[PDB]
């Protein structure tokens, strides 16, 4: 059923990660959302990453802040595309989050998006675009959505 | 023929972008490589982004340094996934490149990877992972590639 | 009619960009203000840049935050002077805005000003100074304006 | 004679500032180049700024690194457009230069360009664009220049 | 009469600069406080720096934020020690203020202190320490002040 | 036999990590050194962390650069003290390394040391200090070592 | 009695440092808490560091902000492991704190933790992990604590 | 005899600190130069700071890099003005040095100068200016020196 997995390290990250989920709902893309902590539930994170392909997921969106290792460790355990959303940390305003996620070494990519809510929104859209590369209907919806916002901004 | 488009603003960026192209070659994914400058050939960039889908491309890999606008402006003109590789700039060592690419606003995602050559490498792998979500053979090749490196590092 | 064009990616940027427009009003420089988004209305942005000179514009003031590409992409499409105002972003406080605007490569300059409201004010003054290089009346107005502030600051110099 | 003044705090900055001057030469815009130090020749800097308009200058390009105060202090003393080129400093790689120049307060704008040589090139182009807002011949030259580079980049687009 | 001159570019900087003035009051060092703007009253700033020595001043404390040029331009026009207090700017939290002040080139030193109120406090103490190098009574007062705080913190 | 485990993601990190090992040799503390990559050998990393205590290790020193997750992921899988050495990365000079290691969330500490070789040296010393809290002979050796350097710097 | 010493430069730091103390209470590890200022009570700091081992302390947790020298100066005066908590400063949000603590030179390590409260929590846990290397009961408690959180996050 | 003390943590800092000493030689101001390490010779540093006034020093110039605590700890032990020169560190290019020195808390000022050699030059000049506040001959020399450089730059 689910094509996209949206995961995060803590329930306090839900404030940020729900934007991604809104986009998936808006585009009618089935997904699952779960708390998976790289540091508090490491084994559970490995099991989630390992089984993702077998369970039918095509893309994983992972949100994390501070020493954000969730996206990269999930990426090291699955060859599904993994999208990393840097959550805005308290002290360093997501600078720590961003560098921990985007600077992955050769071999283990993480598709990194902007810090915060704009990034979460974009993670959902990027997941959609990934599916849209083979699901013509999802691609056509992204074009129509983008054409409506364009008309709205230009004429508003 | 070509599934992935690898573009960059200058021939000097090739030193960085070739790593992505080596990965595509290694995984037998057909691709095209071109110089497309957001600032020196803006119209051409739009024409390249507009037609990408019609031409058969499924993913675009774009590299740029400094005020790196190439990935983002291409992403605004196509709903294909766009992967942005921040090139290491002279003065700010790709920090400017990184922020200009990854901080895209809600509506226009760019899958951002590490600054420099590690990122270029990962851009090629990420493009493969995207294709691998629907091309099992490409996915199987990524798994085998990762398993060989694993064995190599652990036994080495 | 309009000599300056003041543009921005979103209505939320108006809070910042109105400072530039207050300056143009204060100096009686005709201008137009529009929402032009590099990412949400890319084609419209190109059309706005391309036609600027034909429409009579002499300078463009463009405000944007985050991955701020509006000033740079407008500058790549017109040879009118383009002034970029980095809008204070939420997470990185305009640092992302600043670098995305000022670090333009050889061939496509963008006259970059301070982050936020101070930069917006100065964008309006910089546009006026540009016009003032050939309009003596505008230049004289800038001198007078600056002389009044100087007197105002110096005669209110005692902290009491 | 001279329409643009290109100044810098030290001879060592010439390595960076000559890029602006190559552009002015290429476009046949008369200019003058001088060493004017905000910290080592402060009085001379004020004299140079004060008199710029009387001497016929229309734009000033000022390069400085570190605690780069030359562009800002020149801008506080003339209402001609002042373009600031952040010179790449040794320790902070121009980050100090950049912030010292771009973050000018309301009232005293400085048109800030990229750190280093790319910024220097663009300072020359920006000065030309400023003049080009009223000199159609200079504007036409900028359009032609930009059209030739475009063709040059696009026809050498195949990586081989 | 006045031994120290405390100046700043705007009345809004007073919130920060008063701490330095409280210290001078506390140590009975005569001082003057004025608004002197490097960018809005440049000529006046030069005149204030030029005449400082003739007028009897021994130290200048200058506060400024953003592109903070006041301390540095004053320092270039007088050979009195000049203490620069970086005011906390809105966007960059005084980072711009700090670099613009402290990075002065060889030939024109500015004694730079902490960003904000702690620095303002220290500017007053530093000015006293300078005077205390030749005024034993001022030095003795600094020692007693520091000894009282020490006792207060350790026993508190 | 081995009380300390010194690990790193790549052989290229050896240049930095040998400083820690030199200290352990100097102090005659038995240790093991291995390449363990969080991203290239994730499973092996888990196995290494899990079994550390059973194998007799008391402290783990882990070095990594860029998106440095090795120390943190090892720390999430063992309750032995884990010391993180940020390796100096090419583009961001270890700033990415530092933030990815030090900013661990509540529950999973990583004792972080300086970027580069100085940090590596200190990692070995810190591991010794930890052992020295219960091994009086190791503590006495650290004091004597520190006293000799003190005499050397002051008299040199 | 006390095995751990928790110190800080000012009572205002207490808000951050109590997190470490809560952990030590939770784990029933006896400790002492004191205000010890590197800059306001330097002599006292030296005395506290010097005598730590004689007084029976095994680990010292030190919190400081801004130009945070407390952890490092304490570390230069004792060969007990010293854990540095960077307190979130007002202007630079602990970046100054972090760099002033973590960047210790070869010879004088400071085990550095995250900026703020998360770091304080981890400082207490790290101190326990150090004691746990030789106190099996403390180690078992850390494992049980970590297992309960794991079950709580995964099932919650 | 000596009016100024020039100290540093390591002989490798001499490359930077000699510029300050050149200025003092050029201006004929007697001074002493010594290696004093805040971390390797902490007690010796306290003794040097404590006795500075009694020995006749009027100003102390202290150079240090990384976690640069030498200037601040010396400042906490003497009420003589203390000038801090941030040495350019390897990884963070003196950013660490700068923040560790300039962000001193209220009560313990450090007169901070630019990172590197320009700062060292300026430390010597600032010390001179401090003495020049009461030694008319030293002040007159600073004016003449500055007038010669002005003529040289303007006419050169």
Image (cartoon, coloured by chain):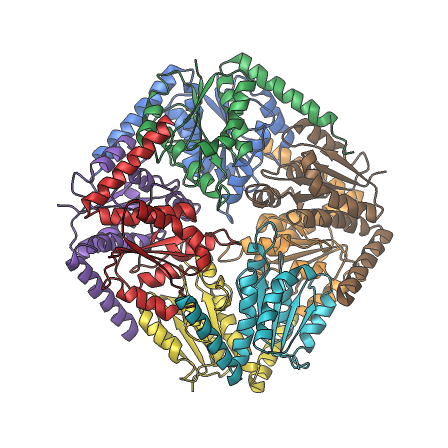
Chain colours: A orange, B brown, C blue, D green, E purple, F cyan, G yellow, H red
Q: Is residue C32 left or right of residue F90?
A: left
Q: Nearer the viewer, residue D66 or C102?
A: D66
Determine the residue positioned at 42% across, 47% down.
Answer: H117
**Considering the image in quadrants, where does the N terminus of chain G appear?**
bottom left
Q: Nearer the viewer, residue D42 or C56?
A: D42
Determine the residue positioned at 40% across, 25% down.
Answer: C25
Q: Is residue G26 left or right of residue A58?
A: left
Look at the picture and state if C62 lies above or below E71. Answer: above
Determine the residue positioned at 39% across, 77% down.
Answer: G50
Q: Is residue A38 visible?
A: no
**Considering the image in quadrants, where does the C terminus of chain G appear?**
bottom right
Q: Is residue F5 left or right of residue E63?
A: right
Residue at the limit of the structure toward the left, as seen here: E1
Percent position (x, y) of residue C53? 55, 18
Quarter of the rendering containing residue B66 = top right
Q: Is residue H30 visible?
A: yes
Percent position (x, y) of residue D123? 50, 27
Percent position (x, y) of residue A96? 55, 56
Quarter of the rendering containing residue G46 = bottom left
Quarter of the rendering containing residue D4 = top left
Look at the picture and state if G76 lies above or below E22. Answer: below
Number of callouts: 0
Look at the picture and state if C126 lies above or below E156. Answer: above
Percent position (x, y) of residue F102? 54, 63
Q: Nearer the viewer, residue H34 or F48?
A: H34
């Amino acid at each position: 059923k689910s094509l996209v997995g949206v995961i995060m390290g803590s329930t306090s990250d839900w404030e940020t990660m729900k934007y991604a989920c809104d986009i998936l709902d808006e585009l009618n893309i089935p997904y699952e959302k779960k708390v998976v902590s790289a540091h508090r539930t490491p084994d559970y994170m490995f099991e989630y990453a390992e089984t993702a392909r077998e369970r039918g997921l095509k893309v994983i969106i992972a949100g994390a802040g501070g020493a954000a290792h969730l996206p990269g460790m999930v990426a090291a355990k699955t060859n599904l595309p993994v999208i990393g959303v840097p959550v805005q940390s308290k002290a360093l305003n997501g600078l720590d989050s961003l560098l921990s996620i985007v600077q992955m070494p050769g071999g283990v990519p993480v598709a990194t998006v902007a810090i915060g809510k704009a990034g979460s929104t974009n993670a959902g859209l990027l997941a959609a675009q990934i599916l849209g590369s083979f699901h013509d209907d999802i691609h056509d919806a992204l074009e129509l959505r983008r054409e409506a916002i364009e008309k709205d901004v230009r004429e508003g």
